Image 1 (cartoon, rainbow, N blue to C red):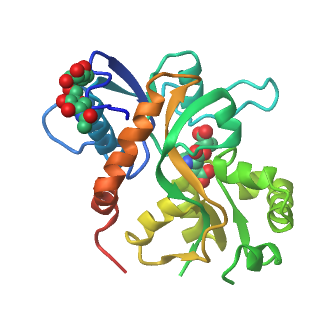
Image 2 (image 1 turned 90 degrees about the vertical axis):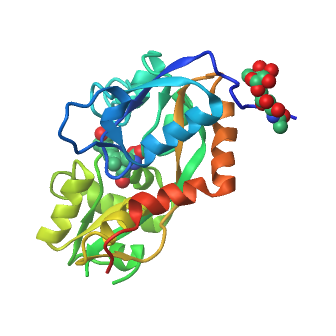
Length: 261
Ligand SMILES: *[C@H]1O[C@H](CO[C@@H]2O[C@@H](C)[C@@H](O)[C@@H](O)[C@@H]2O)[C@@H](O)[C@H](O)[C@H]1NC(C)=O
Ligand SMILES: C/C(=C/C=C/[C@@H](C)C(=O)O)[C@H]1CN[C@H](C(=O)O)[C@H]1CC(=O)O
């Protein structure tokens, strides 16, 4: 068969990540806190877990440039965590980094540790097309993110209809981060095209916000890895193993469940 316990026991790895609730946070505390110890969140538990199985040591580092990884339109150069990996500056990228076609062409991904899809976040119409087929209520996504790239690329009529809308209204309707989008829903009359996984989080934390419709597509977040990295195939197996016993479900339950609505 294929055995993995301690399979990369000798290695010490550099993990790049980005701050995003509730995947990666700085711990709230009162003594000065140091190293890996600074951080917490779903991705942080996932790391601990993957490290226990695969037996490596690791250092967490926030992406220096502070972006996920888009390709520059003008000169076709990669930027965020995606960049960090190519220049081999990091071994692993553990974050809500969507496994994208474009991204997969320059980097290797593990199999998903979470599956999701694009959805609508509105103030408490119920279709992606209920939206595209109209003009009253404005809608948008995070600029140059996986969500946007979906519509930009889509040959399905509905989503290419919607992409035309947002493209024409680029600077008024595309936001620069999740929080900006959330706030823009609460403040204006705006439907935010957001990843279901993150909607589900804010939904049970703010009682005025709801999800409209189901999943427009389906993504996964994968552990990121330089092109052809040896470690990858192992990380995939180590993932499914956690998924198997239902640790992932429990980690999910831990950070997401809470207050209510
Ligand atoms: C495989 O995993 C375990 C391996 O433990 C030790 O460390 C690894 C890196 C190898 O070098 C190996 O020689 C050592 O024994 C085993 O303890 C375990 O029985 C194996 N699991 C299965 C079910 O195949
Ligand atoms: C929260 C988020 C922000 C992305 C911001 C872009 C502008 C970037 O900094 O590269 C990511 C996380 N998952 C999606 C992705 O992998 O691209 C994206 C969220 C989204 O597009 O809805």
